[PDB]
Length: 345
Length: 56
DNA sequence: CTTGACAAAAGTGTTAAATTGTGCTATACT
Image (cartoon, rainbow over all chains, first blue to last red):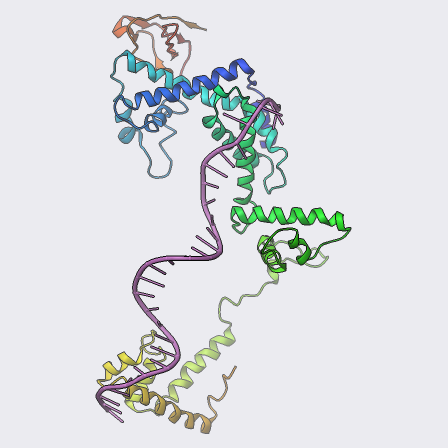
């Protein structure tokens, strides 16, 4: 069971009081500055050796082995960084352990405040995430608030974390819920509007109107800007939604297929494609083969007058009159045979 | 559950390596560990102390 | 079947306005 799971996993590891807390944060910052210290040792970026710590800490072969088909492999772009600073005197080799223990302590403090992160996401439900999702992204917000925290400021990490958890959650909302991607600001304004509506509803004792609701919204807020985006907001509809009151009918089964031309159109189109071929043969060998090049009948791409006149050796003028006369000259055959007089839609 | 192994000159292992009875710990070959388990290297207590363990 | 001339439609390019994606917020809050 996934529900009870996480709860019983975090309930295993205890919390942290001021002692452990302050200490842990100090350990982390010491490891960080230790990295910056060793960043000048071999000339490696503070972020580089930082992740190089992960290689032997939160997994051996599992951190870099599959971040896709390519990443920073253990033998190639890792090993030469693991056994590089590996030969340095005391004044260097010590910062290694400072970074080891700092890096571990980081994850530690995180695990300690996890019993909070979960209890945080509890209010943020209903977002299209049943708990565990919300909690996960919240845990990410914790990871953020972790490396950005400062113990020196004598602030309880429980305060700093919350403001970031609420962030990584309220952010995950817009990037998950609506089936159609709805950008952050969009949803922001949505919640703003819906808040105003759901508020003045009780105030006026009834529902607002696009004019009066957008009125209390601000400048440039007409009936349109609210009613317009109101459409966007609305999510799609499950094709499994039952239609009628009887248990048979499905939603999706009630939708047509206009994507593919209907058989009646297969013959309707294949008919014109021919009937226009036979009524075409009454044209001169020039004014016909040319009359096709201007309709995209030949190579399927349309050939402008300029090029047609280059193909027949004539001029950008001659082809022009050729089309005119050749065309109406067919209009006579059409108006006299009534074979094609349909297709007038 | 563990055994302490104090040192003087640096160490040949980081925090968490897998050792075995008769392996080189620290001090450039002086102090050796007689038992399995991950080696938790401490700076302040100056000890290469190895906790009884089996990498499973 | 044709030449020069020439409106309209179409094209190449820069900039302005608009849209979209991110990072933070520290009393404490498990």
